[PDB]
Image: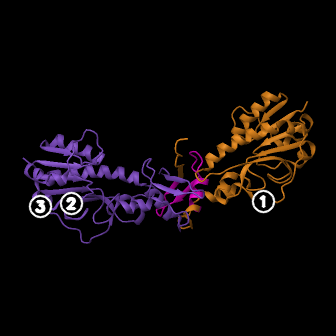
Chain colours: A purple, B orange
Amino acid sequence: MVTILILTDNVHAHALAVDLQARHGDMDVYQSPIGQLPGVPRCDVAERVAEIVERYDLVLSFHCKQRFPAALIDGVRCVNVHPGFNPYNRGWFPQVFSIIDGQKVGVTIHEIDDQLDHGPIIAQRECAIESWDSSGSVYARLMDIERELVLEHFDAIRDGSYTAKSPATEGNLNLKKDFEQLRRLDLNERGTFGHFLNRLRALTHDDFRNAWFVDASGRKVFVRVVLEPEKP
Amino acid sequence: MVTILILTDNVHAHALAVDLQARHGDMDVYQSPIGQLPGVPRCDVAERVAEIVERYDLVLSFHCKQRFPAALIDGVRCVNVHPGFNPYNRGWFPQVFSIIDGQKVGVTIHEIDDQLDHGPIIAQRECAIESWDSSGSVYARLMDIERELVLEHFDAIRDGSYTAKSPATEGNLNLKKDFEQLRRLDLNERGTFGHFLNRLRALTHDDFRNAWFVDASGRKVFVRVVLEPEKPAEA
């Protein structure tokens, strides 16, 4: 008896959403106008507030990066699923920034307020970062944890039977621009080999061409690292 | 009429030798007692000096790492093919060391004397090192260049009709221990990002596990780098 709107542009969250839908039933699964998921219906949130409010009991977003209209937040219960450990490295690509700065990463399910990845926490779970992890390998585990956490908490999210708690501090927020500035490797920058290995593995995600430098002759060169722990 | 002994332990130099033998005829191809080339006959050079000297007119080695017996050098004309640009980064894995120090790398065909990769140069050719090269990618090009250069100068080497010239300087020599020392990445070591990238690419060679660090829990982790230049606009 609970009508749920799911919104996500993320491929892994969408696969999760499709499974929740097969199990729950009264749930629609949409992406935004800029989403790139083929065959997934599209919802322009800013233009659909009264419709969403009239039709749904709960809006459940995954990996949302754009703030919801105040009227939406007020008109219906809005919950977001974020693949970082709030309030640390809120925003873009939490694992990239955690690999670099040592703070916790994980998955957080929280009530939505007017700030990004901010607001009362319903549940969260940490994900360990190993010395040999890259962004891509942490991200993969984060997607498993996300599925594990959401499935465990689904009934309480659907029913509203939790007591959510705001984090104790504001933490820190990373935006797209903070990621873009990390991508560029300054060949002149001094630091430890550990620091440099952290930077390269933080920027390594499957075959994405994230990290780049410009060489002594003006040519752009992309870089990633392959890290392999000795078997125990 | 020139009877040649080729010695090499290297798999690419050996394929080159077999091609030379097909064209030359009067040529035997051997590896050392420690070579790992399957089906390649073995020659213990130190134990075989008198035999080599009587049977052959030229000894031509490729990538030779053990100094030749003095009586051998004196008894028969000996020439080596070394995949570095003498006199710079002589010895082990020149492209590794040149990726790090910016010195020239290449292939050098030289007369053998009593030091490693030292002795009058018959011919050499440089191999450019790109910012995106690894040891592995430079090494593959060095093997092409080696075949190019040796084929070009083979008749002259065979006939002894060249005039070899000693390099003007001693340059420098790397041994196996110098390579092994590079392998351990100290996480506390300080340097530029450029220097560190040079270190990782120098230690990247196909899938060999050359570079490693130990993390704070004592776990050993191996490291390779993948570099790819932005593709030029379509030609």
In what element is the residue under mark 1? loop
Which of the two discs, 3 and 2, labels the residue nearer the N terminus? 3
Which residue position is annotated with label 1?
A: B171
Q: CA distance from mark 3 to mark 1?
A: 76 Å
Residue furthest to the front in view is: B235
Residue B148 to residue A231: above or below: above
Q: Are marks 3 and 1 in contact (CB under 8 Å)?
A: no
Which residue position is annotated with label 3?
A: A74
Q: Residues within 10 Å of mark 1 (few under 14, many from 20)?
A: few
Same-subunit check for callouts 3 and 2: yes
Residue A200 is situated, as x and y percent measured from the top left of the image, at 48, 58
Residue type pointed to by label 2: His
Which residue position is annotated with label 2?
A: A110
Q: Residues within 10 Å of mark 3 (few under 14, many from 20)?
A: few
Q: Which chain does tag 3 point to? A: A
Which of these two is toward me, A27 or B75? A27
Residue type pointed to by label 3: Asp
Q: Which chain does tag 1 point to? A: B
Give yes or no for residue B215 being in the magenta stretch. yes
Q: CA distance from mark 3 to mark 2?
A: 15 Å
In what element is the residue under mark 3? helix
Give yes or no for residue A144 being in the magenta stretch. no
Q: Are marks 3 and 2 in contact (CB under 8 Å)?
A: no
